[PDB]
Image: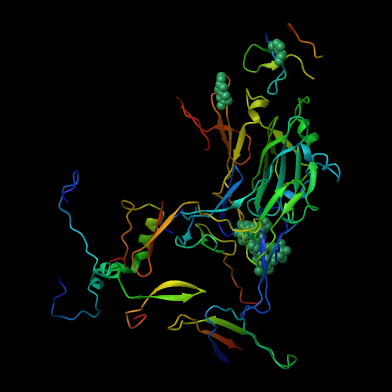
Amino acid sequence: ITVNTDIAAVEQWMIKITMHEGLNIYDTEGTLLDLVREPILQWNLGRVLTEMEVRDLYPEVNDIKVTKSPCANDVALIGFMMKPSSNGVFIGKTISGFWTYKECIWHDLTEIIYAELKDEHQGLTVIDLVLTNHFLVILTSLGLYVSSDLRYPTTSQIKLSRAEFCGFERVDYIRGNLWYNEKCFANRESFEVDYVTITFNRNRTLSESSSCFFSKEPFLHWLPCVFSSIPRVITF
Amino acid sequence: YVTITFNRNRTLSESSSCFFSKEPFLHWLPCVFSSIPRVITF
Amino acid sequence: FYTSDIVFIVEDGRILTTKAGLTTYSELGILKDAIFTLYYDQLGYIHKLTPENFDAGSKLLGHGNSGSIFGKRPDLGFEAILVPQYISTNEMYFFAH
Amino acid sequence: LSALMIPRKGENPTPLVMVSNPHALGFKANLNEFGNTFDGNSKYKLDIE
Amino acid sequence: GRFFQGSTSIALVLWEGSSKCYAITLLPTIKSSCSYLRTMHHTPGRH
Amino acid sequence: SKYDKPYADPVHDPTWRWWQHKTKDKDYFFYLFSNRLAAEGIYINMNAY
Amino acid sequence: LFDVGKERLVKRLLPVGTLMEYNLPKPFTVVNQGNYQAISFTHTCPFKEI
Ligand SMILES: *[C@@H]1O[C@H](CO)[C@@H](O[C@@H]2O[C@H](CO)[C@@H](O[C@@H]3O[C@H](CO[C@@H]4O[C@H](CO)[C@@H](O)[C@H](O[C@@H]5O[C@H](CO)[C@@H](O)[C@H](O)[C@@H]5O)[C@@H]4O)[C@@H](O)[C@H](O[C@@H]4O[C@H](CO)[C@@H](O)[C@H](O)[C@@H]4O[C@@H]4O[C@H](CO)[C@@H](O)[C@H](O)[C@@H]4O)[C@@H]3O)[C@H](O)[C@H]2NC(C)=O)[C@H](O)[C@H]1NC(C)=O
Ligand SMILES: *[C@@H]1O[C@H](CO)[C@@H](O)[C@H](O)[C@H]1NC(C)=O
Ligand SMILES: *[C@@H]1O[C@H](CO)[C@@H](O)[C@H](O)[C@H]1NC(C)=O
């Protein structure tokens, strides 16, 4: 099937079982997924929550978000948005496309996301999250975080970098969306470049006059989407 | 050196209200690094 | 991206569906759960995701049917008086009163 | 060898080729559609090698 | 292609068809690059 | 309208006389067009006429 | 067309086949199907297709 065994974005495979090839009679469809080349699977997302540790969380859940991992589906991440009464970042992982509830292993990322903060503030929930072909972006209640990368496993634990947004407090990050074009880049042609847009609902304060930013592939420089009554950018 | 002092709530974006800079006033760095007493003057 | 299916969720619990590039749509049904979301896998099957509920559908076909979770295909008709009227051998008008 | 098959109008029959002695006779069969009749049904040509 | 340069998508839509059919839209992609199998070899003739 | 001559050309299709002394070298015209180094960026094809 | 705002001289197709098909009053029968009654128009063209 495959002769290369690095870490890269490789598509899934569609499997057809038949009783004969040319005279196709009893067709049955299915999926086959590679494990050793999938980017996201090689890292540990965080501390594993056990059973009956997620059951008490249920009367606190407020909304559900999912990812898709554009090149190969069925390896989605499911994120919980929760009430401000409870605390923690709660993400489950699938590898079989949510066919059984027993397989969605639940993690928690509170330690990793509190590391680059210098102090715990109040309590945080995941607002939105996307999974690009080589990066993971999470807009949580306390700001925006970008994973370092997925193709170079070094510590078996995701290292998040906190994006900077001057003048942005908690009541802005709870109203903000991430937009991304779901396109698969399997063999990685040179012209293919990925973008991510973030949009807030703000008042155009003194510190920042924009409400809409976008960034290229290593999500480090976030530049405003509008340059030099005034309309609002719903989506760029 | 020049010091600048504010009166803030220690928000999410910024944790300091006391900065200072050298003769080229381009790199303004906080005066105190890592209940919390407020610094009136540094 | 398989089967080119698109599904919108609208408050009051309704679910609208279409294919990509078509200029018409349909109403798959209704769903009144408090917190839920819809997911499409690689083969095209649709799953309802809820805390402690990952449902896939009662009736499953070989291909990727997108209406398995809902019970019966709903009646799209309203309540009015229809007056029919012939115009040809195989064509007919209906007037809503 | 070659055979021709026309199915019913709405049904979907699946043909099959079998060998009495598979220990000493192997085959490969290809079923391809060619033409379409006047009424609307489609002729199928299946060739066995 | 036109000349020396990307990618594009070709969409085939059956506008008349119903929304309960399994396959309606077909989306080939055409890339103005070379595949990973496009190589050139030189047989030495010795074997 | 000029093909009314009473002397038989070796080939039909009177555009053969047009595209005969230049048709040996279509590839160079194509190379000059593809890398946009020629004329007004105009590629005059040989089989379009 | 004498209509106010569009008083103008226009040329227009006259679909004779469509008019002939839209000529409605034709012999029919009250045929019994599905333990009910339907209006089935008698076939006048001797052939089905050409
Ligand atoms: C859908 O799924 C299919 C499943 O097959 C998948 O096809 C696979 O795509 C891969 C690319 O993503 C292909 O990998 C490529 O393999 C090339 C070598 O092919 C050789 O073919 C020989 C005869 O068939 C075979 O004997 C040979 O055996 C192998 O040799 C390897 C050493 O070359 C060795 O490591 C193996 O263990 C095995 O012995 C090969 O199979 C490679 O040339 C190609 O590119 C190289 O990649 C490596 C790693 O990054 C790199 O170090 C190396 O320099 C090459 O990079 C570039 O090569 C080009 C030449 O091609 C140079 O010009 C550049 O300068 C670079 O140097 C790559 O690894 C794989 O072969 C293929 N599967 C099969 C069965 O063929 C599709 O891609 C999937 N598609 C989608 C959209 O998902
Ligand atoms: C802008 O400010 C007004 C009052 O100052 C506030 O009501 C409004 O919500 C603000 N806009 C947004 C998008 O929050
Ligand atoms: C901090 O916040 C409290 C209430 O939110 C306010 O009363 C106080 O003035 C703030 N501190 C400063 C220095 O403004």
Name the quadrant containing residue A116. top right
Q: Is residue A56 above or below residue D41?
A: above
Here the colouring is rainbow
Horizontal and vertical percent position of residue G49: 36, 80
Horizontal and vertical percent position of residue D38: 42, 83
Front-lying residue, D31 or D37: D37
Front-lying residue, G4 or B35: G4
Q: Is residue A226 above or below residue C7?
A: above
Asked whether the viewer can see residue F21, the reply is no
Q: Quadrant of the image for the C terminus of chain E?
A: bottom right
Q: Looking at this rendering, what residue extends furthest in the top direction?
A: B41
Q: Residue at x 67, y 64 (%)?
A: C60
Q: Residue at x 57, y 29 (%)?
A: A201
Asked whether the viewer can see residue G6, the reply is yes
Q: Where ligand 1 lies, by quadrant?
A: bottom right
Q: Is residue A181 above or below residue A29?
A: above
Q: Residue at x 31, y 52 (%)?
A: F39
Name the quadrant containing residue F49. bottom left
Front-lying residue, C10 or E23: C10
Q: Residue at x 61, y 42 (%)?
A: A217
Q: Quadrant of the image for the N terminus of chain E?
A: bottom left
Give the left or right position of residue F46, taking residue G10 as reference.
right
Horizontal and vertical percent position of residue A16: 67, 70
Horizontal and vertical percent position of residue A67: 67, 47
